[PDB]
Image (cartoon, rainbow over all chains, first blue to last red; front, side, top):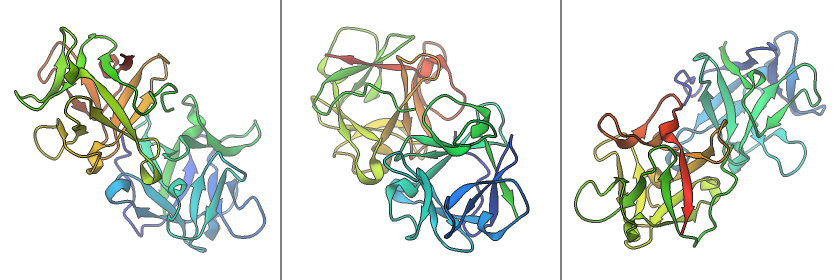
Length: 146
Length: 146
């Protein structure tokens, strides 16, 4: 089931993991350019969505407020999760927000191209990344409106 | 997780529901034109897949062997599940085969355009159809190679 409370285009938010409470950042210098962060609010944690239409209905690109790059999530080469210019030029820039089957206020950030979800955890490296497999709580996210 | 054993293009199969044991048919006369059936093998139960590429990577159109129509699954207007000419001209012609997380030998037939899965049951009308909501065993299918 698609998440029923996806922000409108233009609406700013952070992506905060339910369990760790960490947020995603997306920046242009100092790799890793996309990772998780536990600390104060900074601009590179801010996103809006580009809504897919036509064949991309129910998919979205996740676009950085300060730098305009969109996220990607792939398994073909490193970095697996990253950012790129182009407003969703690449197929692996397109994400589905899939409501959790138990917690209606959380969702997984699912990539159709790579069949992966994003996760945030505290112990096992890599502590942020993408994953194809079973459902775990560390895959659950919130849109934190700002 | 995408079902790991999706038939090659050109390979014929029936779509058989795990629990009811019914198969899907897709025909051109006698509505309903797409429905479930418990009976002898007929050619209108045979399908092959068209593999999506580009924005349709990991999606598939489900094409009738005898009549060439592809399935659709929609919520805009009746019939909700049906067939139509072409090789997936329409966005609701494109399906994802999503492995069940508990029974690795079964999958759901998921439509990205309509956010629905196909189901087969013996109880309430409509006994075959599409559905947006919780996961149930009546949504589980097999590819039956012929």
